[PDB]
């Protein structure tokens, strides 16, 4: 296929290189002339600006640091829009703010142009080998059309279920993993302060929600089924967390996420949830966010 | 075997019931006379106090709400110690402060008495069916001796590797799972506020550290191998967490654990770890706890 | 008066010394024999245990690290209760858990003994000079009776208004000041990271709730009067706190209290309080604590 | 003087009204035509856009919700820069990100234009009466030049000491007061849950760092003098904060700022500061922010 690729950085350059290896014709643009020359050496055609890159391209891929730069590349001076066909598909593979994604897609649709969000998971090492995780936003039609192109850059495609849903599922995944790392560290350092070998804690946690998560263990048959009858009461969870913070404070292991979590359980007790299943914390957070109670 | 059981509550009563079902002779005590009578009706003998329960018992099991009550039952007026044989073994199956466990074991040893910590995982439904997770503290000799008794009450025994290591691994496991529930709720409510179906997020998270945990994914080949070369840089993790909190604050989804987690990443940046792997957060927390850097 | 003093530490020793200086007869006990000897040299009588110290004393003062030790000294082996007259008054000047204070007072009353809570503010340098802040719990009768004794050890007495109210107001004051220190540090370090001289910030904050507090500025005529019509809207407070956290995160100034505070304002916005006065955060916290909205 | 005023909202409209009352000639712009009409009725000249407002103005005032809108009004389509004289002075009175202020000032200087930051303290009622607190950033020359104009809108001018220092001191002040409100609420609700009348707590706190602040009480003679010898040891502060959180958790009073504060004191203990004065928390936060220890 005829592809424009705009943004030839640590991720963009290996992604564009993989597309060339699968026999696509690339017109490439980057403000860094050296990044263009390295792709021309691999078989790309250089463009002077995004509009030139987009002329007669079927797919236009952006891989840029932020939503302001995506907006400039699409709508700015000699932007993609000036060279773009109504039949072409823009694929933004950038990780940007989800509401910026929505406004870019809407602003494109208003001019008769098609744009989808396919941000990626995993590292620049995965970008090189073509083993990225593709979190495919866009319509069902756009995902079907883009799939052959996307599978040149990644090894696994998740259909996120609509325009702007790729950037949203990347955000939820990364929020959870990045914050989980900080909590994981508190548990591991408290373990070391107690002179418990870490392997013993990992062995036990691998068989509980501690190591498997709540999403598929504690939650499905309780809160997610509308049943808050207790397996593990909020009062007992609150008590055990109190003991963990008493130990941490005695042993000078700072546990900011633990301390914050206990005040969430305290709010749940204040709201009358003490004798509910611990999965009711999901309902407490939904109500705290101004959502309508489901149970 | 001849067994004393002290504490016949939601967990203690079914645990004692399972020991009777396997043919042991139980002498039972609880301050709630009705809980005694329910076990006497199943073939237990009554005791008027802990000292009477312990007289001629080989194993003495306590299942009590907190370490002050365990101490009172062992050392208080008409306590276990007054009726206890030096050949007998005390098994505290309570979830109590682990340094209280250490002091109880030491105080017992000073009087010539043997005590081990075997707290349990899983809930009262599992107590009824005899399918508790047994987190066995104590010496190798104590665990070997107790095992036949313990397997009446639980279906799986983990040898925690020493005196006080059962209560330690119970605390680390529960700390992690209890706090993880609050973080899990933030991610799920932010997902709902973004109009992304939860099952799509769970499908993505099931393949990453978000759903599998860091302990066995991100950590083993990086921080735990002494390698902090970046797969996912702390600077990029910190940036993505900032976007997640910007979105949450726009959508009024309160995320106290996420907010606290970003200030931990900010401290890591301040400490010069921005270009290190995100698994370096473990080292940041260790150094924050006054421990010597390993990397 | 005849006084027993149990606990002769950094605070207890100078407090007992001031009572001797005002002409009281003290019987003193501490598990640290050297602390007893220092007071005996100043004219105290040594006692071998709390019961001996209490024998024929009119006032019994405890100044101890925690409520378990106060309980042991009153009710334990050779405890005060074994030497205590029903006409005597026990004064716990310790900072302990307020519900432990309530139970000690009740347990003493059950045995026919009178006990009050009079913890103190200010530090060991004030204990030496007799310039402590006296936070007097107890009945009006107990405060009247104790006052002449207490004014040997402190320069200002606040009548906290009942049994257990002294330890309650000590806890609220210390909670606020101890946590406020951590927040103050975040503001000061963000100030330094921005290259703004601290003196300029303190000059501005001295004229606003930042340096004067909300209790007597923002709150009285708004939330405390039942009026949540906005002077400074929660939405604008939330926005400005977002900017502060953006700056802190760009400059790697860790601000855990600020970060936590923004999620409280976020909860207030979710509850529909965005266009209310910022003093409505008090009502948000009351509702979050399961109290009936005012 | 000839003044352009862009942003005629809750603050901007009364500020522009006070400039008209003091005899200035105003050219006004707001995207809300009704807000323009209210000022035109008081004698302002309407402008169709920021460039038109700025034409022949000596002073150009912006009072806008955020730094993106300030940038759009100055540099965007029909922006101030298109109508601006190199002899004119731009005054941003908005509360925006201070590093955005620095970049706006620098971007203006690059085009030969002069810009200063003068955000305001106090509320819309003060904007109406002309009694705002003026937090004047800019060079000494710019503050001197702007002062006569500024004193039409505010009653008190603080010279913050340089370009970008007005927005920095506004941000430190608001950060502190906004976060302090949430901590104040936790102390007040714990007070209610303990059945202690709030006025008794306020009376005690008004005499301590709890109600007076640490900046001018605890800090000057200790950390700010390089003296960390203890008046109130970090270990004792950490212990008392533990008791307050135990009580709050027993009484289901959520205290997220208190909880976060205890983990900062815990970090201080881990770093070897347990036996230092509580004012050493400032040094702990500085070191946590990657600053060189004092
Ligand atoms: N780096 C990772 O480990 C990783 C992992 C997964 C996803 N991501 C996402 O990938 C992106 C990071 O991209 P990267 O690492 O290639 O960044 P990079 O900074 O290395 O490359 C960005 C490129 O864009 C170019 N560019 C900037 N403005 C431009 C413009 N107006 N027109 C044309 N080119 C322009 C730059 O010259 C540069 O070559 C983010 O969106 C990030 O979240 C990163
Ligand atoms: N319930 C759960 O889901 C669960 C799960 C795992 C572990 N645990 C642990 O089990 C313990 C609590 O057990 P439970 O759930 O049966 O509690 P419970 O409150 O249902 O029962 C506690 C029993 O102890 C008795 N008791 C209290 N003081 C006593 C005394 N001085 N002497 C004798 N008896 C006394 C009470 O009367 C009561 O029958 C805790 O340590 C808890 O952490 C509970
Ligand atoms: N130190 C301060 O800055 C300060 C300020 C206000 C209030 N307080 C409160 O004062 C109380 C005591 O304070 P401190 O600074 O004097 O403590 P400290 O530890 O210096 O003194 C306590 C004394 O009690 C003695 N003691 C311990 N157990 C005893 C027992 N069973 N019988 C007799 N004596 C016993 C110890 O030997 C010691 O001398 C605490 O509640 C503390 O919070 C202290
Ligand atoms: N309201 C307060 O209590 C208070 C206190 C002190 C400081 N401030 C600061 O005052 C500033 C403005 O606040 P306000 O309360 O007057 O806000 P406001 O929302 O009431 O007014 C903003 C005005 O700007 C106008 N505007 C928006 N975009 C524009 C554009 N491109 N060109 C021209 N006009 C435009 C809007 O129509 C509106 O009239 C903010 O930075 C705020 O932080 C407010």
Image (spheres, coloured by chain):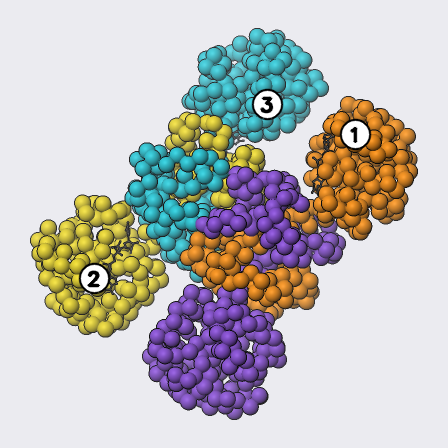
Chain colours: A yellow, B cyan, C orange, D purple
Task: Find the distance from the CA under tag 1 to the CA under tag 3.
Answer: 31 Å
Q: Nearer the viewer, mark 1 or mark 3?
A: 1
Q: Which residue is mark 3?
A: B103
Task: Find the distance from the CA under tag 2 to the CA under tag 1.
Answer: 80 Å
Residue shown at 47% from the left, 69% from the top: D164
What is the chain letter for disc 1? Answer: C
Frontmost residue, D78 versus B190: D78
Q: Which residue is mark 1?
A: C36
Give the quarter of the image for residue C205.
Answer: bottom right
Q: Is residue B247 visible?
A: yes
Picture layout, residue C4 above or below residue B91: below
Residue shown at 43% from the left, 56% from the top: C251
Residue shown at 30% from the left, 56% from the top: A95
Quadrant for ligand 3? top right
Secondary structure of the residue carrying tag 1 is helix
Residue shown at 57% from the left, 8% from the top: B87
Frontmost residue, A29 versus C41: C41
Q: Are marks 2 and 1 on the same chain?
A: no
Classed neighbour count for the residue bearing mark 2: other residues with Cα under 10 Å, few (<14), some (14–19), many (≥20): few
Ligand 1 within 8 Å of disc 2? The answer is: yes
Q: Nearer the viewer, mark 2 or mark 3?
A: 2
Q: Are marks 1 and 3 on the same chain?
A: no
């Amino acid at each position: 296929a005829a592809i424009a690729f705009i943004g030839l950085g640590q991720m963009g350059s290996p992604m564009a290189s993989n597309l060339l290896q699968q026999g696509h014709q690339l017109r490439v643009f980057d403000v860094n002339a050296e990044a263009v020359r390295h792709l021309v050496d691999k078989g790309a055609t250089p463009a002077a600006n995004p509009a030139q890159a987009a002329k007669d391209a079927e797919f236009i891929i952006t891989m840029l640091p932020n939503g302001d730069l995506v907006r400039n590349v699409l709508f700015g001076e000699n932007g993609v829009c000036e060279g773009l066909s109504t039949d072409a598909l823009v694929i933004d593979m950038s990780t940007i703010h989800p509401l910026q994604t929505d406004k870019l897609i809407a602003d494109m649709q208003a001019k008769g142009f098609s744009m989808m969000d396919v941000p990626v998971g995993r590292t620049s090492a995965n970008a090189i080998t073509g083993t990225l995780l593709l979190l495919a936003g866009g319509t069902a039609e756009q995902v079907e059309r883009a799939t052959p192109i996307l599978m040149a850059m990644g090894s696994e495609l998740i259909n996120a279920g609509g325009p702007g849903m790729g950037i949203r599922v990347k955000l939820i995944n990364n929020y959870m993993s990045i914050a989980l790392n900080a909590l994981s560290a508190e548990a591991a350092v408290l373990c070391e302060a107690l002179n418990l070998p870490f392997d013993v804690a990992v062995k036990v946690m691998s068989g509980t929600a501690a190591g498997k998560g709540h999403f598929t263990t504690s939650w499905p048959n309780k809160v997610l089924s509308g049943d808050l009858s207790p397996a593990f009461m909020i009062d007992l969870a609150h008590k055990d967390l109190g003991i963990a913070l008493d130990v941490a404070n005695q042993l000078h292991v700072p546990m900011p996420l633990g301390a914050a979590s206990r005040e969430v359980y305290s709010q749940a007790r204040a709201a009358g949830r003490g004798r509910q299943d611990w999965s009711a914390i999901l309902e407490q957070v939904r109500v705290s966010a101004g959502m309508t109670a489901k149970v």
